[PDB]
Image (cartoon, coloured by chain):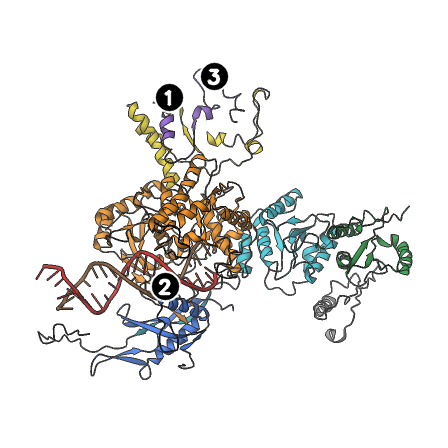
Chain colours: A cyan, B orange, C blue, D green, E yellow, F purple, H red, I brown
DNA sequence: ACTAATAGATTAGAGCCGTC
RNA sequence: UGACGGCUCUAAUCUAUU
C-alpha cells in the first residue's frame, strides 16, 4: 500500500496536480494521476480498482470549483469512501482545497467532515502540512528523490516535447554567384578621365 | 548545419534539468537560505503597490499554457525561502518633495538630485536603522521615469518648476561605495491589474505573462540575497571566460575615450565580474591591455589556486595585433588563451520550407575551423515556441586569435545561455559574460569616482 | 500582387505593407548576394510613410501574423521574381560582361528537428 | 428554491417512524425527503443526499437515537447541513427530533 | 572550535545548577531562528600566512598589519563575492591578542 | 596597541557587523594549562555566557 | 445495441460478475453512453449475491 | 601635409515594438 | 530600469583611391 491517489478534474486541476504530484513524487511518494502515465486506455477502470484497493494507501483529493460536481472525481471519491471502510484507516481520504472561487461552504459531503489541507492562501504551507501529516501517520514512503519527479516530468510532460533525428532542408537569404567576368581591367587613364568626374 | 544540443542547468539537491522556470517550480534553488529581508522604500501610494502584490507572489500564479509559460507555485514552494511583510523599512518618500524635485527642467541635475533624494534615504537606513536588508527595494513612480530619463523630455501642460543622465545606472553605481544590492521597479510592473494606463487594457503586461512575469520579478529579487538558484554543469574546469564590451564613457567630448568592463566567469560556478581599464582607436592599449589580464586572470590564483588552462575571452569587437600580443607575455604562459568575437555581423537567416514554425535553436553552420554560426535563438522543443517571435539571426562566432575546436566552442557559448539572473527565460540569446557586461559597463561609466574590485552581479 | 501564388504586397488596417529586400554582396564565406527581409508601408500603395518610428511600429505589428512560411515564400517569390531566364540572374558589368546569380537561395541540411506537435 | 423539508435519519432503524411521520407529514402537506422511501434508488446515495442538503433542503430535521448519532453516514449529513446552516445563517436549520425514548 | 560550539547551543546544555547558572533549551527553542553549520564562509588564513606577518616585531606596524590581513578579505567577500554573511565571526587565536595588547 | 579598535573602525566604510571572538571564550573545553586546571573556568557560565 | 435501446442496466451484482472483462466491457460501454445519454439512473446494480 | 574622400567592414547608442 | 527578442535609427572609426 504505497500509492497516493489524486482525484481531480482532468484538464483543469492539471496545473496544481502537476505541481502537487511531481512535488509528491519529488518528495518521494508514489502517486496515481491521469497525467503521470502514457499508453493509457484500458488502464482507465478495471485497474484503478486494483491500484486503489491494493496499492493506494492515501487519497489526496483535489478540491476545487472544477473537481466539484464532476462525474470522474465523484465516482473516484465514492470509491475512496468505500475503500476507507474495509481497512481500519479513517485518515485515508485527505481533501485539498485549492480554488478561491470554491467557498468552504460548497464542499461535497464525502469530505465535509474531513479536515482538508489548505492551499488557497499558499501552496508551500499546504505542501509542508502534507509532509508532517504523513510523518505523524507513519505513511509508507521511500527516500526522498526528485529525480523520479523529473523522470515523470521528462517521460510524461516532455514526451512529445523533445528533438528527433530527422533530415530537414532549410532555405536561406544567400544567393550564390555562379560565374564571374573573366578579367578585371584597370584602365590606365592618366589625366584622361576627369579628376572630379564622380565615376559613380 | 550540425545541431548543437541544448545545455543543462542544475537546481536543488544537485539535480539537472533544462528549464529555469520549470526546474525551480518543481526542484528549487541549490543553496539553502531561510528568509529574505526586503528593505522597501517608495512613495506612500507605492507602498500599497508592493505590499499586497508581494503576497500574490507566494500564491500560485497560473499560466494559460504550462508548456510555453511554465508553472509558478509560489515563493516558499519554489525558492524554499520565506518572504513576508516584515523588514519593510518603508522610508516614506512624500510626493511634495518629489513634486518640487521631479519637474525641474535640467537634464542631469534633475536626475542627479532626484536619485540623490532616493539615495540619502536608503543609505542612512542601512547605516543607522535595525533591519538586515538584503534586497533593497526602491519602488519608483511612473511620472518620474516618463520625465527623468536619457534625453529627458518634459511636456508643457503643467510647467511650474524651472532649472550618465540615466536614473538606473546612476542609482546602482553610487551604491558600490555602500555595497548594497537593490531592485528597482518602474510603471506597472506590479500594478498592471488596475493601472489601465492608456485605456482600460493593461498595456504594460497581461495575465499570460503574469505566470512568469512574477518569475522574473522573484528571481531578480532572489539571487541578490546570496542564493545560487542554478549553476552550469557542462562547463569544464580550468576555463576562463572574459566577456568584455567596450563602452563609450562620454557623450560630448573625446568620442574615442572609452572603457571596458570585462566580466570573468569562473569554473567553480562563480558569475564573477572584473573591472577593466579606460582605454582611449576602440582598442585596449598595452598599458591598459596588460592590466586587464594581469588583474582579471589573477583571480584564478586565489579563487582556485592555479591559472586556467583555457582562457575564452569574448567580445563584440575584433582584435588587432597590439591587444593580443600584450595578452601573451603579461601573464599567460603554458596556458591557452582564445579570443572569440560574437556579433550579429551579417544576416544569415534560415527558413523551413516544409512546416510553418521557424528554425529550431541550436544550429551551427561551419565556414571554417575558426569561424561558424550559432542559432542560439529560435524554436525550442520543450516550450514548443520560438524564443524569438520573428525570424532569428545567429551569433557569428569566429576565433579571432588562437586555435580551438569551434564545435567545442559553440556548445560552450550555448552553455552560457541560461545564466540570465535578470529574467526567467529558457535561454538567453547572448553569452552571460557578454550580455551582463553591457549593464555593468553602463554602471561603471555612470560616475568617474569608483574603485570597484571584481564585484558580483547583485549590485548591478 | 502575387508571384507564383505568393502575395508580396498587401493590406494592414490603413497601411499597405510591401515586402522589400536589401542586397549586400560578399566574398565570404563564398561569393554570394546576401539578402535581407524588410516590410515597408505605403499610405496609398505608391508613397512610403515618412516616419521611421511609425514604420518601425508598423513593421513590428505587421510581422505579428507572419510565420516562417509567410517569410520564406515572400522572400523566394520576390527573389525568383528577379530570376532572369530559368535558374539564374545576371548582373551586367559591361556591354558583354554579365554576372549570373542563382535565383534559388542556398540549401542547407540538418539532421535534428522537432516533430511539429501542432 | 428550498421547499423540501429534508429529514435525516439512520438506516431502517427509524424508517418505520419516518414514513409514519411522512404519511402524516406529506399527508398534511410538508414536502418530506427521506433516504428510505424518497431516496432515488439505483443512483448515488452519497451525491443525492448532498445535492438535496446543499441546494434543495429547506429544513434539516435529524432524528436523535443511540443508533442515529454515531453513524458516519448520519454525521456526514450534519456537517454539510451545518455548513449550509452557516450559509443560511440559521441556527434552527438543524432541528434534532428526540424520537427514541 | 565553532564546528563544536556552533551546533552545541542548538541542543540544551545543563550547567552545575540552573538556579544560579541557568541552562537554555537551545537556539531554535529560545531565540526562534536558524543558526547552524550552513552558510559557513570558512576563509582560511593559514598560520604560515599569519606567521609571515606575525614574525615582524615592530608592534607599531605589525598590529596594523595583522588587522589588514583580516579586513581585506571581509570587504572583498562583502563586495567582490557571491556569498552573503549576516554577522562575521573573526576567531582570532589567543596568541594574536596575547602579543598585540598594550 | 590592541587591534580591537582598528579592526572595527576600518569597517565603518563597509558597515558589516563583525562579532569579534576569541579561542579562549569559544574553546573553554579543550584549553588546558600546565598544572591541569584551566585559567578560564567558563564551564558554569556556559549557560548565560552562551546567552 | 447499447446506444440504440439499452434502457436500464440492471446488473447482476454477483460475487463473480465484476472481475469479468465482458461485463466490464458492457459497463465501460455503459459508462461512455451514460455521459452521451446524460443519464444518472442508467445503472441499477441489483445486489443478488448473498 | 593632409586638406576632401566614396566605398569596404566593423563598431556602440537607443528608441521602439512584439510577447518567449 | 521584471524582461527577452527582433529589427530600426544615428554616429564614429580603420583601411586604399580623386
Q: Is residue A77 left or right of residue B88?
A: right
On the image, the x and y values in percent for residue A56 come to 67, 53
Q: Does label 1 lie on the same chain as label 3?
A: no
Q: Pick the residue in front: B322 or A150.
A: B322
* Label 3 crowd bin: few (<14), some (14–19), many (20+), radius 10 Å: few
> Could you tell me which residue is drawn at 85 percent across and 50 percent down?
D63
Above or below, I9 relative to B292: below
Which chain hosts label 2? Answer: B
From this viewpoint, which residue is outermost toward the bottom? C85
Q: Which residue is mark 1?
A: E98
State the separation of the CA atoms marked 3 and 2.
75 Å
Q: Which residue is mark 2?
A: B394
Q: Which residue is mark 3?
A: F37
* Label 2 crowd bin: few (<14), some (14–19), many (20+), radius 10 Å: many
User: Judging from the image, what secondary structure is the residue with disc 2 in?
Assistant: loop
On the image, the x and y values in percent for residue A117 come to 65, 48
Q: Are marks 1 and 2 in contact (CB under 8 Å)?
A: no
Amino acid at each position: 500500500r504505497n500509492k497516493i491517489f489524486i482525484s481531480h478534474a482532468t484538464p483543469d486541476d492539471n496545473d496544481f496536480t502537476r505541481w502537487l504530484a511531481l512535488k509528491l513524487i519529488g518528495l518521494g511518494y508514489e502517486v496515481w494521476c491521469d497525467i503521470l502515465f502514457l499508453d493509457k486506455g484500458v488502464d482507465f477502470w478495471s485497474n484503478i480498482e486494483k491500484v486503489i484497493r491494493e496499492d493506494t494507501c492515501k487519497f489526496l483529493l483535489v478540491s476545487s470549483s472544477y473537481s466539484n460536481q464532476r462525474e470522474g472525481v465523484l465516482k473516484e471519491l465514492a470509491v475512496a469512501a468505500k475503500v476507507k471502510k474495509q481497512l481500519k484507516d479513517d485518515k485515508f481520504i485527505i481533501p485539498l482545497a485549492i480554488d478561491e472561487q470554491l467557498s468552504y461552504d460548497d464542499i461535497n459531503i464525502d469530505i465535509v467532515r474531513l479536515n482538508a489541507i489548505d492551499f488557497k492562501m499558499s501552496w508551500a504551507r499546504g505542501l509542508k502540512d502534507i509532509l508532517e501529516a504523513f510523518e505523524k501517520q507513519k505513511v509508507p514512503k521511500e527516500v526522498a528523490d526528485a529525480s523520479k519527479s523529473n523522470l515523470l516530468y521528462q517521460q510524461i510532460f516532455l514526451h512529445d516535447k523533445s528533438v528527433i533525428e530527422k533530415e530537414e532542408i532549410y532555405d536561406s537569404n544567400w544567393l550564390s554567384i555562379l560565374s564571374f567576368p573573366e578579367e578585371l581591367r584597370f584602365h590606365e587613364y592618366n589625366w584622361m578621365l576627369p579628376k572630379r568626374f564622380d565615376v559613380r | 548545419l550540425i545541431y548543437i544540443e541544448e545545455p543543462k542547468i542544475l537546481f536543488a539537491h544537485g539535480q539537472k534539468c533544462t528549464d529555469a522556470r520549470d526546474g525551480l517550480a518543481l526542484f528549487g534553488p541549490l543553496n539553502n537560505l531561510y528568509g529574505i529581508k526586503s528593505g522597501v522604500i517608495g512613495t506612500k501610494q507605492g507602498l500599497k503597490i508592493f505590499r499586497d502584490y508581494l503576497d500574490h507572489i507566494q500564491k500560485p500564479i497560473y499560466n494559460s499554457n504550462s508548456i510555453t509559460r511554465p508553472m509558478f507555485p509560489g515563493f516558499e514552494a519554489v525558492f524554499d525561502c520565506k518572504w513576508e511583510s516584515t523588514g519593510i523599512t518603508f522610508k516614506e518618500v512624500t510626493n511634495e518633495d518629489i513634486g518640487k524635485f521631479l519637474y525641474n527642467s535640467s537634464t542631469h541635475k534633475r536626475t542627479y538630485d532626484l536619485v540623490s533624494l532616493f539615495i540619502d534615504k536608503i543609505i542612512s537606513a542601512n547605516k543607522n536603522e535595525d533591519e538586515n536588508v538584503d534586497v533593497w527595494f526602491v519602488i519608483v513612480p511612473d511620472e518620474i521615469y516618463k520625465y527623468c530619463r536619457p534625453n529627458s523630455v518634459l511636456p508643457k501642460e503643467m510647467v511650474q518648476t524651472k532649472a550618465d543622465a540615466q536614473f538606473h545606472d546612476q542609482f546602482k553605481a553610487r551604491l558600490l561605495k555602500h555595497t548594497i544590492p537593490t531592485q528597482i521597479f518602474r510603471e506597472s510592473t506590479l500594478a498592471w491589474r488596475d493601472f489601465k494606463n492608456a485605456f482600460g487594457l493593461p498595456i504594460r503586461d497581461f495575465s499570460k505573462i503574469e505566470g512568469h512575469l512574477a518569475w522574473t520579478i522573484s528571481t531578480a529579487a532572489f539571487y541578490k540575497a546570496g542564493g545560487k538558484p542554478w549553476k552550469l554543469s557542462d562547463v569544464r574546469n580550468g576555463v576562463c571566460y572574459l566577456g568584455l564590451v567596450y563602452k563609450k564613457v562620454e557623450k560630448s567630448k573625446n568620442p574615442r575615450n572609452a572603457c571596458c568592463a570585462a566580466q570573468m566567469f569562473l569554473d567553480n560556478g562563480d558569475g564573477t565580474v572584473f573591472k577593466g581599464e579606460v582605454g582611449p582607436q576602440y582598442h585596449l592599449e598595452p598599458k591598459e591591455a596588460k592590466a586587464l589580464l594581469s588583474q582579471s586572470l589573477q583571480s584564478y590564483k586565489e579563487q582556485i589556486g592555479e591559472y586556467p588552462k583555457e582562457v575564452f575571452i569574448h567580445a563584440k569587437t575584433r582584435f588587432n595585433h597590439q591587444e593580443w600580443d600584450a595578452f601573451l607575455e603579461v601573464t599567460p604562459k603554458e596556458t591557452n588563451l582564445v579570443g572569440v568575437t560574437i556579433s550579429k555581423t551579417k544576416p544569415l537567416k534560415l527558413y523551413k520550407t516544409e512546416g510553418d514554425y521557424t528554425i529550431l535553436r541550436g544550429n551551427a553552420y561551419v565556414v571554417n575551423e575558426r569561424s561558424a554560426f550559432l542559432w542560439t535563438v529560435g524554436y525550442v522543443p520543450k516550450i514548443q515556441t520560438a524564443l524569438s517571435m520573428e525570424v532569428p539571426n545567429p551569433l557569428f562566432i569566429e576565433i579571432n586569435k588562437g586555435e580551438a575546436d569551434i564545435k567545442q566552442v559553440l556548445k560552450d557559448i550555448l552553455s552560457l545561455t541560461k545564466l540570465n539572473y535578470n529574467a526567467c527565460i529558457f535561454a538567453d540569446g547572448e553569452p552571460v559574460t557578454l550580455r551582463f557586461a553591457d549593464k555593468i559597463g553602463e554602471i561603471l561609466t555612470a560616475s568617474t569616482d569608483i574603485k570597484t574590485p571584481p564585484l558580483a552581479f547583485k549590485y548591478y | 500582387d502575387k508571384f507564383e501564388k505568393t502575395m508580396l504586397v498587401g493590406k494592414q488596417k490603413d497601411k499597405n505593407w510591401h515586402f522589400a529586400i536589401s542586397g549586400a554582396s560578399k566574398l565570404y564565406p563564398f561569393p554570394v548576394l546576401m539578402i535581407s527581409s524588410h516590410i515597408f508601408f505605403t499610405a496609398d500603395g505608391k508613397k512610403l510613410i515618412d516616419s521611421s518610428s511609425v514604420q518601425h511600429s508598423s513593421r513590428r505589428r505587421q510581422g505579428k501574423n507572419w510565420w516562417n512560411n509567410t517569410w520564406r515564400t515572400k522572400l523566394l517569390a520576390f527573389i525568383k521574381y528577379l530570376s532572369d531566364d530559368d535558374t539564374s540572374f545576371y548582373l551586367e558589368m559591361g556591354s558583354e560582361e554579365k554576372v549570373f546569380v542563382s535565383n534559388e537561395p542556398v540549401k542547407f541540411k540538418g539532421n535534428v528537428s522537432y516533430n511539429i506537435p501542432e | 428554491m428550498r421547499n423540501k423539508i429534508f429529514i435525516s435519519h439512520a438506516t431502517p432503524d427509524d424508517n418505520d417512524f419516518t414514513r409514519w411521520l411522512a404519511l402524516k407529514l406529506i399527508g398534511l402537506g410538508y414536502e418530506v425527503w427521506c433516504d428510505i422511501l424518497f431516496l432515488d434508488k439505483g443512483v448515488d446515495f452519497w451525491s443525492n443526499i448532498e445535492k438535496v442538503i446543499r441546494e434543495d433542503t429547506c429544513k434539516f430535521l435529524l432524528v436523535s437515537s443511540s443508533y442515529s448519532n454515531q453513524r458516519e453516514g448520519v454525521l456526514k449529513e450534519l456537517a454539510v447541513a451545518a455548513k449550509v446552516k452557516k450559509q443560511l445563517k440559521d441556527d434552527k436549520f438543524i432541528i434534532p427530533l428526540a424520537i427514541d425514548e
